[PDB]
Image (cartoon, rainbow, N blue to C red):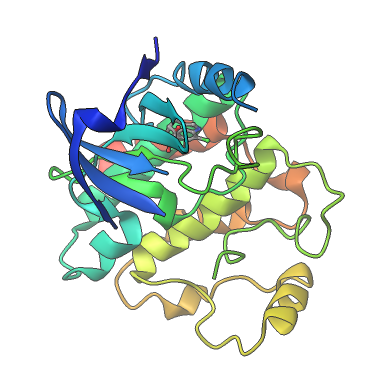
Length: 253
Ligand SMILES: CN1C(=O)N[C@H](Cc2c[nH]c3c(Cl)cccc23)C1=O
């Protein structure tokens, strides 16, 4: 069940519009700050309970304040971790890839298409374990009513009519795979938003040759399959896991 929280249960906040908040009992939490259906959508999102998914612990529904309260991941997002001293060994990277696949397969099993999967939505703890988050509320309908295109499937670029599918998340994952090995955002040479959109829609993808740090040939083949222009040519997350998991256990531990 979802917990109705009061802003009096918090001692102070600091904007990391997300914010770190200190609860007087449950400790550290993240706070992101139609009255009736808002709490039912909170109950629905509170059902997303998995080890690789940031849990919605509670909601603040007060006169003037409407906030979503989530579990805190002490290291921040994936990109910030990757750029902070690029020591991150290959076996840890492979483990992060496997955890992302597991979280995405869980979400799709609950009928949830993310739509905004990117390193900014992959949060990290002190042991380098990850959880998928939806900080921009891409998967919300009521709560959302009250460099980002790098991870967007070409079918949605310049086409808002296109219904997002489970294959839209597979494409985002493919670009996340490239970013994990490159330790940076793709398309550094792109000059304009319009040219980048048209280049991607015409077949352009992140530079596979721009990975100075070693990346196994099998992972490069996987990202090339996941970022295929035809959504139907992309594999599903359990299909990715069925090939990645045995590679991870026999080559990366
Ligand atoms: C904003 N928010 C989260 O990041 N985690 C919780 C639960 C949640 C809702 N939608 C999610 C998606 Cl699409 C991915 C991971 C967690 C969630 C939440 O409310």
